Image (cartoon, rainbow, N blue to C red):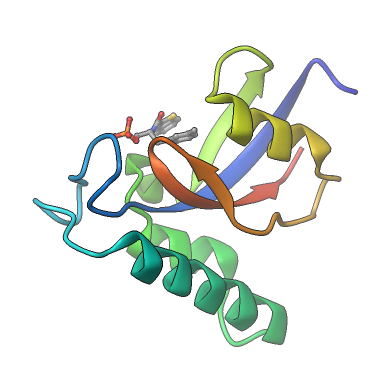
Length: 113
Ligand SMILES: Cc1cccc(C[C@H](COP(=O)([O-])[O-])NC(=O)c2cc3ccccc3s2)c1
């Protein structure tokens, strides 16, 4: 395992998120069921080729990293919420996670380095 990995992600928050607001929405009103529906919708469009991971994140990610087309830069273990960390370090470079759940909300993650 490398010291650090580089990943991009797409976050979908819900009303029960630890901080139910984002750059794109003053109050997150969607239900967590709806948030996971969106994430799985995104996964299937990216698998089919109909959508690009990084374009989706720049438009709809509730993380401010959307301005970076989803890129979070490099990080080591011990910095991110543990479920996020574990999924990231389990990916191969170029691979995409399934749904990842954290206190911030629901993620799909793409390891780039
Ligand atoms: C577990 C987790 C991983 C990444 C992001 C979040 C959401 C978190 C905001 O969700 P919140 O704290 O409101 O519940 N964003 C960040 O930690 C980061 C944003 C950026 C922007 C640019 C570059 C690096 C970073 S790290 C949570």
